[PDB]
Structure formats: structure tokens, C-alpha cells
Length: 292
Ligand SMILES: CCCCCCCC/C=C\CCCCCCCC(=O)O
Ligand SMILES: CCCCCCCCO[C@@H]1O[C@H](CO)[C@@H](O)[C@H](O)[C@H]1O
Image 1 (cartoon, rainbow, N blue to C red):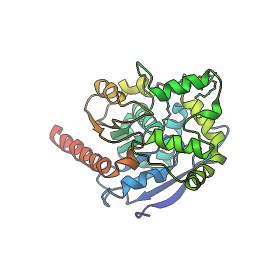
Image 2 (cartoon, rainbow, N blue to C red):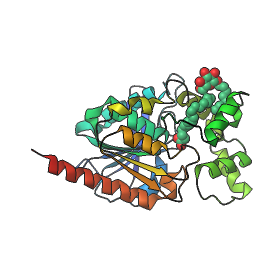
Image 3 (tube, rainbow, N blue to C red):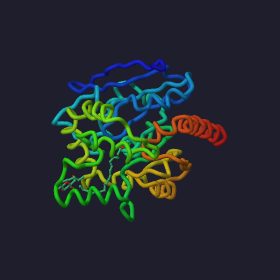
């Protein structure tokens, strides 16, 4: 369990499920946002290598796992950013500025959140964030455009419904992926099948005109030290995105990881956790120097 405890917090009829350890102290608290179709426990690999003197919060994103799934919820990046601000206000996480960490769709929400509520965030860590406008499409984005041409919504690579589709999703999302036995693939996809209608609705909403490039559209408003962590072998969100952010945001440190695909937090958890803590210390040192 790593000392992480699951709790639920309510905003009227909406509930957020989150895991946590430690308590608000002198250092900035850390709020972690997972990616598309995942949940708060994808952060456990990194938490295992994080120090115990930090206040860590890992929240299930809107409609995922223990957080409310409602047909009336606004699943656009703007609406998810707003839900995250309600959750933050619920826990009083912004009592003093906090460090905000996000991966992929969570990375996009994190970037847009720092642009919407700049006084809430002390520093940002964006792990292969979605929401950028690339000059050319990688094979995955060319596949999505091809699927749009036949409206084959049942073939979205990140929404598998069969063992063979699950094996393709596992290959696309990680650099090293040896073949898994059919029984294990079947078990992995069965836990996701009841949630595929929601993932299909969420996916179409985050790739819609209003959300597809919202991080790129808001990155001029990010005013805090930002760390970018990206895997050079990312087959989902191309690693060229790291330079687009770095050249558009001041005080930006880029960490390109070798032998690493889209699932950074699962593939390189030790290096990722080390980079997270090192960046936190360098931000504190520059803040102590800048005084007066
Ligand atoms: C149906 C329209 C097709 C056009 C696509 C336009 C560009 C957007 C394409 C891909 C972005 C995918 C972002 C999904 C979240 C990343 C996965 C994750 O969170 O791990
Ligand atoms: C990933 C593509 C799978 C097949 C999608 C079938 C067509 C869905 O429809 C399209 O979805 C887009 C994305 O939300 C919208 O931008 C378009 O307006 C809409 O017509």
C-alpha cells in the first residue's frame, strides 16, 4: 500500500476518490493526475521511490474509478480542469501553492490548470502531456484519422475490447512489451470492458476541436518553473512535444528518457521519482536565491 490511504471527498452530488500519505507541511504538497482510462494507482510505481516526508495526493480523474461518472459532467479539458479546482478547494490543497504533476491527458489538465489558476501552483511537472499541435502526425494519430474516415469508433487503439486488441494497446503504450499469455490479456480487458462506453465518450471529447490543442493554446499563460519528462520511444504522444513546450515556457527543464515509451511512470519509475524530487529542490534553491 506504500502508506497510501483511499478517501472520498464530496462537492454537492459529485465525489472525488483519492489516495494520500503525509500531511500539509513546509514543503509544497504534490497533486498527481493520471492519464486516459487509468486511475490514481498508476502513480504507485513512482510513489514507491518517493521520500516519506512529502504530502502526496493521487486523484481519480472525472468519470474514472472512484470519482463520479455522470452523463452531465463536462469531459472537455476545460471541464476537467474545473473539476480538479473543485477537488483542490475541497481538500484546501491550494492553502499555499502546490506542486502539480500530470501524465498524458492528466499532463494536459495540469498544464491548463496552471494557466487558469496561476496562484495555486508553485511548480509543474508534465510527463508526456497531451494537448499539443504537432506539424506532422505520428502513426497513432494517422490511425485515428484513418478510423474517422470509416467511423470505426470500436477500433480506437486505446479502447481494446478483445485480447488481441489488449496486446496491441500494451505494445503501443510501452517500449518493451514481451507477449502476454491469452488468459492474462483476457483478464486485463475484462476489467475495462464495462467502462469502454465511458472511455469512448471521453476519448472523442478530449480529441474534439475544443480540447485537442488546449495545452498548446494555454502554454503562454504558464508562469511557474516547469519540468517536462518524456520517453524518446513514445508511440502515442510524440517526444517532439517536449521542445515545443520548452521553447514556449520560461524556466523549463526537459528530461528525455531513453528506452521509454508512453507509460513513463510504469517504465522508468525510479528515474522519474528522482527527477521529480531533484526538480523540486532546484526550484526551492532558485527561490531562496531570488529573495529580496
Ligand atoms: C477523430 C479525430 C482524429 C484527429 C486527431 C487529432 C489529434 C489528436 C490525436 C491524438 C491525441 C490523443 C490524446 C489521448 C490521451 C493520451 C493517452 C493517455 O492519456 O495516456
Ligand atoms: C479516433 C477516431 C475513431 C472514429 C471516430 C468516428 C467519428 C466521430 O465523429 C467525429 O469525432 C471527432 C472527434 O471527437 C469530432 O471532431 C468530429 O466533429 C466528429 O464528427
